[PDB]
Amino acid sequence: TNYLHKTLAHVPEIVERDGSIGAWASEGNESGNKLFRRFRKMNARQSKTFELEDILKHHWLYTSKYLQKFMEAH
DNA sequence: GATCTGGCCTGTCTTACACAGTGGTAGTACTCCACTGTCTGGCTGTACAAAAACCCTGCAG
Ligand SMILES: [Ca+2]
């Protein structure tokens, strides 16, 4: 199997090349698709010319350190 | 084999059923900038009088 060669063959080499493995997973991005879905449901403009423009604008807003920092939630 | 007739099909006309909700854009009717000088009315040191509701008291029964 492919996964087996990967996990036996370069793991020490890669964690030497970088210093971790999970710290470069695409994992998080598959989560963020959830986000996209939700936005499309609720903050749509119902116009395919703009729908993406609006979605991207709201998304970017959602992913700024600034506004999250305002989200204290001690 | 001619005839007939109820039941079936096509086409018809009529009453319903989703299409909100979301963002960008604009006109527009409603509201504070700075500058002002002035006045009323709450505040404050005690002393003075006026109401209120009870508690005792006293006379009356
Ligand atoms: Ca209806």
Image: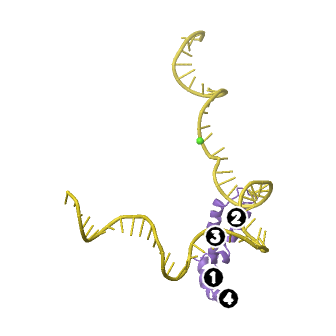
Chain colours: A purple, B yellow
Residue A57 visible in the current orientation: yes
Q: Say the numbered circle drawn on residue A23.
A: 1
Report whether A3 appears left or right of B24.
left
Q: Which residue is mark 3?
A: A32
Q: Please state which of residues A7 and A57 is positioned toward the viewer in this rendering.
A: A57
Q: Amino acid at mark 3?
A: Gly
Q: State how far apart marks 3 and 2 are (Cα).
A: 13 Å
Quarter of image, ligand 1: top right
Q: Is residue A30 above or below residue B25?
A: below
How crowded is the residue under tag 3: few (<14 C-alpha within 10 Å), some, or many (20+)?
Answer: few
Q: Is residue B13 above or below residue B47?
A: above
C-alpha gap between disc 4 and disc 3:
28 Å
Name which residue type carries label 4: Arg
Question: Which of pointers 1 and 4 lies earlier in the amino acid sequence?
Answer: 4
Q: Secondary structure at mark 3?
A: helix
Q: Which residue is mark 2?
A: A55
Do tag 1 and tag 3 residues touch (Cβ < 8 Å)? no
In percent of width and height, residue B57 lies at 25, 70
How many numbered discs sit on the rendered protein? 4
Q: Nearer the viewer, mark 1 or mark 2?
A: 2
